[PDB]
Image (cartoon, rainbow over all chains, first blue to last red; front, side, top):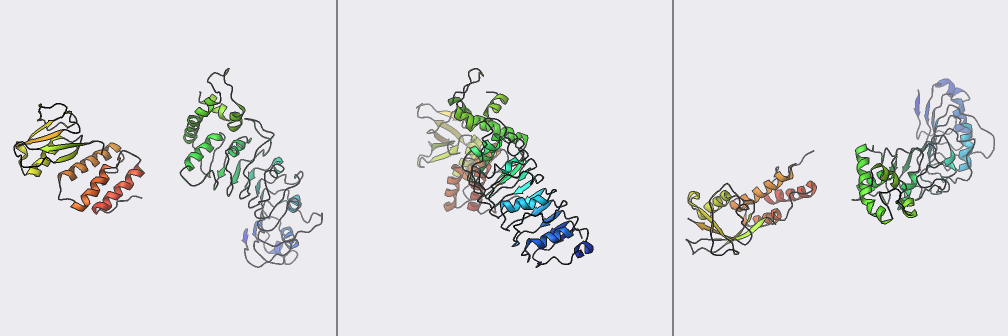
Length: 386
Length: 73
């Protein structure tokens, strides 16, 4: 048994000292979530009894951590540790990760974590730091955890923040914070400014991205436009909204961005001459990557004819008016009249008279042509002779 | 109706114009109280435009002439 799942199985005690190591010594995954565990010493004993514990899941358990400063067990084999809906703090997290030198994934969702100090010797190998559903974590708390060299994965969502700038990074410069953050999950956020993407573009190694459910990336008619703007803002981006960004789509987004912002670039003092290019500070701060792009890509009803119908031979009929298309051929009108008057189409004579030229009658003989070729305009009349 | 929404917009426009001409020619195809709405819809529709905009209008004509709506995967 390598993968053990004991979710909602009522587990409160640990058992015998050595029974778990003797019954199933090849245990690699443990899913002891939502159990009857009311203390942390039991989980510590269970983890100590295992030697190949690679994944340990003990979320949704009401546990009380000891206040002592003694390292209660060391798990060098533990890598993935999920701790969600457990009510943990920053100090407890730092005390727990102090004994896990091989910890590579850590989940901390719905815990109300208040970051205060900077982890120095601890958290030196943790890559994923899922800090979701934490309204206490703001922008000032993400600066301290940004000095982790091994931090590569950051799932920070439903946090409430709407700005993440970088004071150590200027216009078009890379920031020292987050040296390996390549994908930060963004959802349930109230981002209503375009400076967030411009600040995230300054990351040293940013690739994937996911900005779902936001006031700027709503599921409306402006979703594609906002997606293209986000793609054109971050040049090193390779994935947006869990979707691969093709080179053609990126080129199209950048071209649309340039075409839409050329007016604002020229109104701020831009020019094709590098010696005369004097942009303002506001345009440089709002669009740091605009200079790179400028250097790369350089600097049936209307066709209707309301005409009347007359019959010189039969004056008892009324002068009716029809609306026929302009591209209608003569043969179609002849066939219409044939059935209309129950008259053979073989002996049908067609003519038109325009009010601009009174007294002149131009005949219509060729059936292969159209009404547009005979200069038939709107307001003319059709004469039917048979 | 299947040709009314073709991939080529010129074919769509030609089919619409030909259908309008045939409806103006023959009068025993559609009733008197139905032909008026058909002519009003066919005249006030730009068949050389976004297919999503045009399609919606063609489904309308089918429902106005007693024709099942043809659909694709």
